[PDB]
Image (cartoon, rainbow, N blue to C red):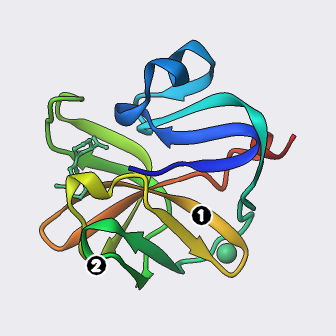
Amino acid sequence: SGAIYVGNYRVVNRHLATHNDWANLVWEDSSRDLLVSSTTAQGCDTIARCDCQTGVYYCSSRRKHYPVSFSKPSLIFVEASEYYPARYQSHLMLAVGHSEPGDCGGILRCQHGVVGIVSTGGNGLVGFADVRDLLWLDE
Ligand SMILES: Cc1cnccc1CC(=O)N1CCC[C@H](C(N)=O)C1
Ligand SMILES: [Zn+2]
């Protein structure tokens, strides 16, 4: 679990969105596993606007942060689950690192701010849904 709070927005994994998230829907993209809902309170996370390929992510299954090198956002094949059929997930970045299903929502950050959130994993690889292109999150 985990979310990004920037301005009047809450960014979560689309497969983990709540009833409240859907009742206050701003935008969602099944192909990205992202959903953004509105909030009454003001958020202070800073979104990175960069092409960083190194950063640190929070791994709840280990109660630890890990430094990683990650790939640029791309279309990557993702196995079927109770949430989605087998498909290509877009805007996804991979790194060599530990992750388990309850790890989705963990933040990946570089020196510039929030890069994205944990969205996939398995086989010693963790996948992060990028948020750096969503420029509207700041306005
Ligand atoms: C096995 C594992 C390890 N770390 C994080 C997550 C996981 C599970 C996993 O990859 N997915 C299940 C939930 C939906 C995901 C998606 N974006 O389609 C895919
Ligand atoms: Zn950066």
- Mark linked to residue 69: none
Q: Residues within 10 Å of mark 2 (few under 14, many from 20)?
A: some
Q: Quadrant of residue 46?
A: bottom right
Q: Quadrant of residue 17?
A: top left
Label 1 secondary element? strand
- What residue type is disc 2 on? Val
Look at 35% across and 53% down and name the residue there: 104
- Give the side of residue 136 with respect to residue 96, left or right: right
Residue wearing tag 1: 115
- In this view, 120 is above or below 59: above
Mark 2 and mark 1 in contact (Cβ < 8 Å)?
Answer: no
N-terminal-most mark, 1 or 2: 2
Q: Quadrant of residue 50?
A: bottom right
Residue wearing tag 2: 96
Look at 26% across and 76% down and name the residue there: 62
- Give the side of residue 52 with respect to residue 122, left or right: right
Mark pair 1, 2: CA separation: 17 Å
The reply to whether the residue tagged 1 has its Cβ within 8 angstroms of ligand 2 is yes
The residue nearer to you, when weighing 89 against 10, is: 10
